[PDB]
Every structure is written in structure tokens, then in C-alpha cells.
Length: 38
Length: 149
Length: 6
Image (cartoon, rainbow over the protein chains, first blue to last red):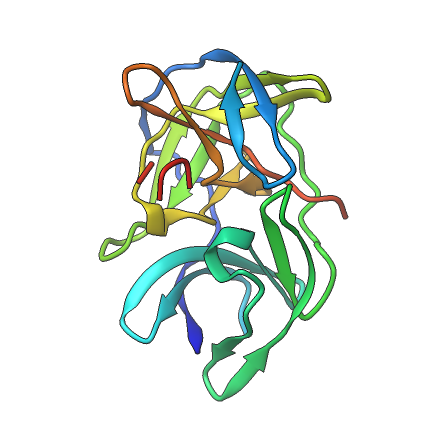
């Protein structure tokens, strides 16, 4: 009932915008697949 | 059929994204819940999946095996609902867990971007975007979620 | 995010 449609090629882009920080976070993963912060 | 990145639609609305590689379609469990998918006139059936990892593969076992090297910047190939695919480069942080460190990207895209691939400099898929945490200010950080080949 | 953390 869901369907898939192509969206692009998988390639690295040389021009790409660079953003976001690089946090080091203490985390737990439960059996339901949910991450949480410790 | 062709290798590439694909939108996952419900007939219509984009609820996620996935990667076709080596004849196998890879997405996150929370996108499809393991339901069958249509590709043209064909049907894709789930082959492998794991709720705790939040991953599912169709038509074969998980094929993506590249790993973040812990040092280099990566690119999220974000495929947001209603928008063209776009590459965003970032230096991952890490989720420190009792079972090891997992690279994590501090990039915030909508729910239906779930399953978008994260790439190394060689263009290999090192994981999928969209299983993460919300920090105190509301910001999102996604694990770089990778399966076992 | 936005279905929570997903």
C-alpha cells in the first residue's frame, strides 16, 4: 500500500553546505529502539 | 529497480526514504513497520529487520556495511517531503553508550526524511538518518544508524 | 525531529 519513487543518485557533493555542531552525548538505547539522554 | 535513494509514500504523502543497493531496499523500521512496498507493478517484501536497531531491508539481507571512520566529515543526503534531494555536510558528534560510541549528526529535518542516507567521502552509505534524541533546547541529533552485513 | 525523536 506504500510505494517507492526514485529521488536521486547517491553521491557526495563537492559544493555542499556545511552546518551542525558535533555534540558528545551520553545516551541509552532501549529495546523499543528509542534513544534517550542519560 | 535502479540503485539510488527513494521516497517512501503512502497513497499521497512521503513518510520516509530508503536506499536501493545490490537489489535490496533499506529503510528504517519506523517508516514501514515491515509492511510490503510497491515499486511500479512489483511488490517488495521484508526480508530482515530489527526494532531495536530501527532498520528493515526488503528482498534480501542488509547490504550497507561502510562505517564512519570517527574523524572525517560526512554528508546527509536529505530527501525531505516535497523538496529535492540535497547534500548537507557536517562533522558528526557521538552518542556514548554502554555498547560503544555511535556517530551522530546534529541536523534537523522533518519526520518524512527518515531513512535518508548518510555518506562518507567515497559516497558509501555509512548509515541512515532519523533515529535520535532531543536535547534540552529542543534541537535534534540523529544517530548514524547502520546495520550488519 | 517531529513523530518525536523519529
